[PDB]
């Protein structure tokens, strides 16, 4: 097994190539905890946060995942793509309708213009719902693990929202169209701001960072093996 | 089996290296029993405790796990990272909503400034919940073992709260946003205060003490074997 | 099988060594039956017993396990560590909340100063709880065996309470913070008073008497075998 000592020399150079081609400041994950929350009844919940624009050569800071309201940093003359990663629990307070429709509306700063709308059917927990002991044995003994693997509504929206730093505010509206529910947003829910590169492949690599490392470390094995043949 | 008598000589030297590089006073676990408890209805429960600052060369004492209110000792000119280890049982008194959201708020001593906020979905015990005999056979015969492995809500927050000894008081707020519940905090719940070292690897070793010993005693086997080859 | 006749000569000498190094009067188990019981509603149940101090060379008596109120004998100028072994059944009289929190408070004789506080989550029997025939087959046919293996709340607190013989009275408070329950204390529940030796290893051997015999009789096998080699 001589492949174990040479694979670090491949992963290090691939990591250096990835950071050279995709800088670390090209993507920013902004959790919804860092937004401002406005709860209503005719619009659901509102996730609005102002945008701060910094000039070139200013070392774009990252968003601290501390749950505090922070301005979203974006490069001034740059166009960003938004990846909405939303995980939430729906809990029926009334009418116990087990399946509902979640309305997702994205606005930007003549008051606010809507730039994205979508619907996602979501399963909602009812008081009559019970958890069988078969699910405990298979889906992990922990009740929270069973709820996460069974009732957690995961909503991913990538490469569909375009935002410019010239706009001052961005708002996200979440509403259920059938009945009022208790929406528990998972703390890992957030919006990832990606720089939209014109090379095409870089945008795909940003969206698939985990898959990109696997493909890169599997495709450098031919470079590793070609020096063996010579 | 000649490896059994030489492994103590490796674990002893690795322990000496660990204590030389990470002193025993670099981390302090302060259980929530040693805080002051203030129970409300508009903020939940409050875990506040004053800070005592001692000068250099004063032999930082540890926190006695006796459940008595003790001041938190921190070095004067040192910045500490807080690891919140929180285990608790949620028990529904009313409305028997099986899943709730726990709000964790951390303050510090112009009255109090919030330095951390987060949410954690938690499972709550209801009166209709029953424990199947299948869970008794698999998750240990003891009822408390089944509750610990099934209903205990474990919340770990590491490397996200930064505290300075210049501040006098630190507060921790726990609240459920949906309904009022009976929160039974596990006696092992507490906050671990770690010194933030600038070397980077030392901070990682403090956070992963159990894993660090395993890696160290597995990586010294090459030093053990190299003297065999010579 | 010649090891069967020589192992008594090893266990006898190890027992003699244990009694020479740890005298028989170095530990005293005082069951809670021998305390005085005061039942309240704002403090739960109170386990208070006065201390008798005898001078040196007085042959410290043991506590008779007869359920009668007896003074606790401790050496005059000696510091004792308390090991609280508490087994109890919780039975819900009202509100049938299946899980509760037990508050343990230890005082000593300006009226009484608290020296230890802790909480232990305990499972409580409800009237709706039923015992499946599967548990009868596996956890012993006897109903009391199933309750002991399933519902008995075992609370062990060792090496956390320090008491001096200069104090006259020691009190133990047991209370459930959620609801009033019927606490049935197991007759074997009690407090073990250990002498705190400065050698460190003796304190560990007192706390692990059963494990200490096993380790000692397994470590004297090398002394047994070394005379075979010579």
Image (tube, coloured by chain):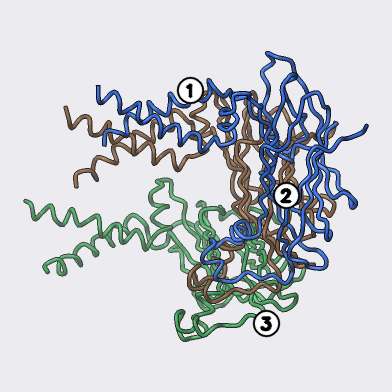
Chain colours: A blue, B brown, C green
- Residue B111 visible: yes
Q: Quadrant of residue A14?
A: top left
Outermost residue toward the right?
A110
Disc 2 vs disc 3: which is toward the camera? 2
* Disc 3/disc 1 C-alpha distance (Å): 66 Å
- Residue A141 marker: none
Alpha-carbon distance for marks 2 and 3? 37 Å
Q: With C171 as the anchor, is C55 left or right in this view?
A: left
Whether callout 2 and callout 3 share a subunit is answered no
Please name the residue that numbered disc 1 is placed on: A16
Circles 2 and 3: CB atoms closer than 8 Å: no
Of pointers 2 and 1, the one earlier in the residue sequence: 1
Label 3 packing within 10 angstroms: few (<14), some (14-19), many (20+): few
On the image, numbered disc 2 is attached to which residue?
A185
Residue ID for mark 3: C127
View extreme (top): residue: A57
**Quadrant in which residue A84 is drawn:** top right
Q: Would you say the residues marked 2 and 1 are in contact, meaning their CB atoms lie under 8 Å apart?
A: no
Q: Nearer the viewer, mark 2 or mark 1?
A: 1
Of all chains, the one bearing label 2 is A
Residue B37 location (% of width, % of height): 74, 50
Q: Position of residue A108 (x, y in %)?
A: 83, 33
Q: Are marks 2 and 1 on the same chain?
A: yes
Q: Which residue is drawn at the image coordinates 75% and 38% (left, top)?
A: B107
């Amino acid at each position: 097994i001589q492949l174990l000592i040479i694979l670090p020399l491949s992963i290090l150079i691939y990591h250096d190539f990835y950071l050279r081609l995709l800088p670390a400041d090209s993507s920013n994950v902004v959790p919804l905890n860092t937004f401002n929350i406005l709860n209503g009844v005719q619009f659901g919940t509102k996730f609005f946060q102002s945008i701060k624009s910094i000039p070139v050569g200013t070392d774009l800071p990252q968003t601290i995942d501390n749950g505090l309201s922070q301005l979203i940093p974006m490069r001034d003359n740059m166009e960003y793509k938004l990846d909405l990663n939303l995980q939430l629990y729906c809990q029926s307070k009334t009418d116990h309708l087990n399946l509902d429709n979640l309305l997702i509306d994205v606005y930007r700063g003549s008051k606010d213009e809507k730039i994205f709308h979508t619907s996602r059917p979501i399963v909602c927990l009812a008081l009559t719902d019970s958890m069988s002991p078969q699910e405990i044995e298979q889906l992990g003994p922990s009740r929270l693990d069973v709820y996460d693997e069974e009732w957690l509504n995961t909503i991913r929206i990538e490469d569909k929202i375009s935002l410019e730093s010239s706009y001052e505010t961005i708002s996200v509206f979440l509403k259920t169209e059938i009945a009022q529910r208790n929406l528990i947003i998972h703390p890992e829910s957030g919006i990832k701001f990606r720089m939209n590169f014109e090379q095409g492949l870089r945008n795909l690599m940003l969206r698939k960072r985990f898959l990109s490392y696997i493909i890169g470390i599997s495709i450098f094995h031919c470079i590793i093996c070609v020096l063996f043949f010579i």
